[PDB]
Image (spheres, coloured by chain):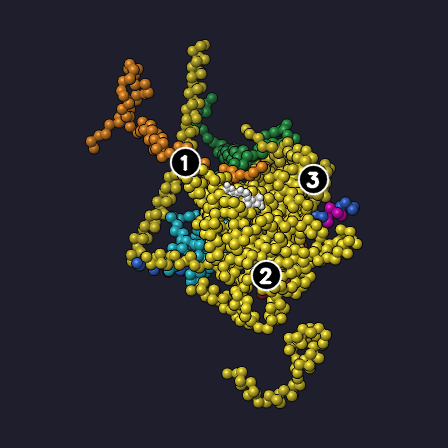
Amino acid sequence: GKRAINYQILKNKGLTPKRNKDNRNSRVKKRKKYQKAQKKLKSVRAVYSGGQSGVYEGEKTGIKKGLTRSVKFK
Amino acid sequence: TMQRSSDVNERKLHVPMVDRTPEDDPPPFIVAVVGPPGTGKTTLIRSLVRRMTKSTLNDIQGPITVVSGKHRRLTFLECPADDLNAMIDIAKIADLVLLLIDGNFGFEMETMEFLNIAQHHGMPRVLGVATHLDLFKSQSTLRASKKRLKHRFWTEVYQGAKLFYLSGVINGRYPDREILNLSRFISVMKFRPLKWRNEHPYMLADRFTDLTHPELIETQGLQIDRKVAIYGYLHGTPLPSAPGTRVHIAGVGDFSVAQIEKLPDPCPTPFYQQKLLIYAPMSNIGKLIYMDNISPEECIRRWRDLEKFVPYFDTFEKLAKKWKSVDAIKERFLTWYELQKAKISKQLEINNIEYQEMTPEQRQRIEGFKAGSYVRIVFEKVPMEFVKNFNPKFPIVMGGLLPTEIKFGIVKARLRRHRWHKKILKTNDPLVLSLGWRRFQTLPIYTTTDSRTRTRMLKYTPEHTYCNAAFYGPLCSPNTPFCGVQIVANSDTGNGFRIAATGIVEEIDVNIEIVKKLKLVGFPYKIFKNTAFIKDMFSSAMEVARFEGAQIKTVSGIRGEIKRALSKPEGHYRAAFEDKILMSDIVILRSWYPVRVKKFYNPVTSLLLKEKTEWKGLRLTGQIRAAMNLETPSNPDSAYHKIEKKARSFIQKVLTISKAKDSKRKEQKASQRKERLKKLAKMEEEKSQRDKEKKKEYFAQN
Amino acid sequence: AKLVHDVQKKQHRERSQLTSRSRYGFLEKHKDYVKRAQDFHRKQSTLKVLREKAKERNPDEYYHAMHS
Amino acid sequence: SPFGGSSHAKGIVLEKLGIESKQPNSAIRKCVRVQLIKNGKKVTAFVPNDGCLNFVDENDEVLLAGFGRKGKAKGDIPGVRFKVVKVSGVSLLALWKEKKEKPR
Amino acid sequence: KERKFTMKEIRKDAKFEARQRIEEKNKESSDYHAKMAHIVNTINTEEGAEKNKYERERKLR
Amino acid sequence: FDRTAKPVPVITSEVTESLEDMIRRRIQDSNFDDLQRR
Ligand SMILES: Nc1nc2c(ncn2[C@@H]2O[C@H](COP(=O)(O)OP(=O)(O)OP(=O)(O)O)[C@@H](O)[C@H]2O)c(=O)[nH]1
Ligand SMILES: [Mg+2]
């Protein structure tokens, strides 16, 4: 029959936004920012990803005729 | 470091306040040992009296007044750790609080409630005593518990407060080194002024006698409202000596004083003023004017009709002839904070320098027993149960009343659910208030100004911010804090908090207008273009004829007035709108019915029960509903809801997949194109304002 | 979000249609109203522009396509 | 520098300027009339968040600081140079996020 | 005839108190706009004077 | 409650007195704003 104090009165926090388990450990947030930005620049360049892994199944995602991604000399 | 030299001398400048603690007979500064049940209090009291007067005290009860040091003394009080009905007024009366925590348990909610009550009602000098360090040999864990308790305590009270730690008890008394280094601190105390204890004459009772006739009580038979002498010790502002003063002692309600009397002081002054120690109880022309008998003109002829305003005069010719020459009247004719402190201190100094005069006027009939005078008070008509079941454990505080705080009526305060109370406060659910000296259960009504035009009734308090509130009760002065408790009985406390509503009274009145938005509601049944006959919101054409001209709006957001009653289908009527409504709409008025506050008022009347606690006042609405087991009145249409050939067949399937996939891809690209457009709008607006700042900074060199 | 709480920007759910009028159900709130009203305004405007051309029909028009 | 040399000045609030502004959380609602103590003068301070305006009532020994707008707002008034940062001992940011408690 | 009398009288009452409270509401709204505008531009100008004075004193040095 | 528009302005002897002294002051000025032969 002896009282106690609960968690929020012991910690004395409250009325904060919902923060992030990714935001807790800085090594993790500087990992889940990189491997997103690692997968981001599969959309501005076309980076090397090992090469011909299986047998050559074709280029598998579309080749278009009227497009030249070659920087030209003015 | 001139910036630091001009920045650290802003710690001095505060609000100028006045003290009224005179330097001739200062009262014993009431300190108040309070905390959890079980640990601490009585052994700490025994140790402090054993180190301050070299004599023990077994079976202590009630308030002691011990002496410490040369000039001034102090007063202890073992407050019981089971009732807010003692905890609240102890926090209202106290000046220092040595506050007990036990380090093998963490904090506790009784000292939590005490610290919140002190924080609202006016901060005394708090000083933490962490006892019960039987923790372990692991001095790492001892340092850990002391560090975490110190950081939590410095967050709860001012950061930097003293937290004296005590070890185990050596045969009844505490370690005397720690009692030494605590007693030196409370000898170098240095208190501060507070507005309540510098505006109200307040006294702690330490002796309590019933000078009512034994033959009279034996011939009346345990029925009388007796007469009672409180032998006590007043603090604060001077309790005015003329009998007839309204004085509220706590937990029974107010009375008027019958006669008061100054006693021999039972505590030391300095011995030079003695010539030229624990006390532990419960264990001409002025009299010519003010003489009642004589008439005023007989008074002035012994010395030597004001509706007529004009001053008196003699014969016009007489004083004109006297003042044909008027040379008899030729003798008449011909920083900021230290400034404010000098102003009020020079006021107090000239007050004292014309107080230091003849004793019957200037001590007990012009200002009346200033501060620090052991006085007996008597009250007749004090009820029976007070003296029948008086307990020496409980404190008896008593504060006088200003002329404004005996009247009754409504009062409009601001309120807020205390942020650790686990449940919010429904309106018309009664609660106990420590508004000033009186503590009372009353029914509030929580209102808010909807953007400051009218005061409508909320059905609930807001969840974390303030709101206005109005309730019947004793009309205290404006701008004062007050706490509000829920149920006070210790049969229902469990594991939850007890303080519910902190707040501040700012405004009193005698009648409040306060509305509640009821919405008249009807349905359309013959919908035209631009007008509609609406149905079964008014029972008669007389009601429609009163309400002709009103703005209504549907649930779709279209306005429209109503015009005239229809004739034959007597309930129905005709209204004009923005454009054509659907049939599945609801027309809505807007209307305000003035609700009135309930005139309930019941003080706690705490120290009259046999039990001294367990004062069940009015129960909450939820628990009387659970007591007579009615369900909570849900409304079934009000609950929310979560609203809302092979080759040819194959080619048709492929096309009807692909066109819908590309359709929603296109609409998603358009949706995000809208946000890219808004982002570019913000960027161009910021860039344009930056460049129009730069183009005039380029020209301000002219 | 500058200086607000999440409890200050909690969600307001919308109330249903009453069961007493559930035969012609689906109470119709403000977004559905504006999606009705702008559509009706557009239909009225195209009706009035073809009515205006009808009131100025100019009864002597002729093209090669009007032989059948 | 804006008041002698100090960066902060204790002050006494006269009255909540603009309680009758109907639009909630507006510039003319979020002002107080602070009596600066260091030279005994009037100034108009700018307490943030009208929901936490109502901590300070009257002579709450408030502690001011500068404001320093980092751009241009929609309906902000100019002239207010001072914001409230601490009231009666505690910081009203901590009060508005309800960690501490205002003492009286 | 009494029904016609009471309906005519209550609608005359409605039109009368309609007119008086609506001119009262517009009058108090206009005076509120006047008071609010007055305090906002006096707090604008009287403080902007010393704001520009302190900015002139700072930008020199 | 609240209402949309001001009601019909009822014609009282005070408002016809103000209209009559308006028009009689106006034609005492003879400031009637008619057309002209132009
Ligand atoms: N080991 C140890 N025991 C303690 C310590 N402090 C108090 N106690 C024990 O607690 C018991 C209760 O003593 P008190 O604290 O004086 O009791 P109280 O103050 O009257 O508290 P209540 O009975 O609830 O009113 C004592 O008999 C002690 O044995 C401590 O620091 N160490
Ligand atoms: Mg005890």
In the image, is the residue at mark 2 within 8 Å of ligand 2 by its beta carbon? no
In the image, is the residue at mark 3 within 8 Å of ligand 1 by its beta carbon? no
Q: Nearer the viewer, residue B214 or B675?
A: B214
Q: Against C58, is A64 above or below? A: above
Q: Colour of chain D?
A: cyan
Q: Nearer the viewer, residue B322 or A43?
A: B322
Q: Residue at label 2? A: B266
Amino acid carrying label 1: it is Glu
Report the residue at 44% width, 16% height from top.
B653
**Residue B190: where, in percent of width, then height?**
48, 58
Q: Which residues are magenta?
A: E5-9
Q: Nearer the viewer, residue D100 or C60?
A: D100
- Quarter occupied by residue A55: top left
Q: Colour of chain F?
A: red
Q: Residue at label 3? A: B538
Report the residue at 43% width, 38% height from top.
B137
Q: Secondary structure at mark 1?
A: helix
Nearer to us: label 1 or label 2: 2
Q: Colour of chain A?
A: orange
Report the disc number at residue B675. Answer: 1
Drawn side of residue A1 relative to residue B228, left or right: left
Q: Colour of chain E?
A: blue
Q: Which chain identifier belongs to the yellow chain?
A: B
Report the residue at 31% width, 53% height from top.
B697
Chain letter of the residue beneath label 2 in the structure image: B
Q: Against B317, is B252 above or below? A: above
Quarter of the figure with the N terminus of chain B: bottom left
Q: Which chain identifier belongs to the green chain?
A: C
Q: Confirm whether the magenta stretch covers residue B61.
A: no
Q: How far separated are the C-alphas under marks 1 and 2?
A: 82 Å
- Quarter occupied by residue B267: bottom right
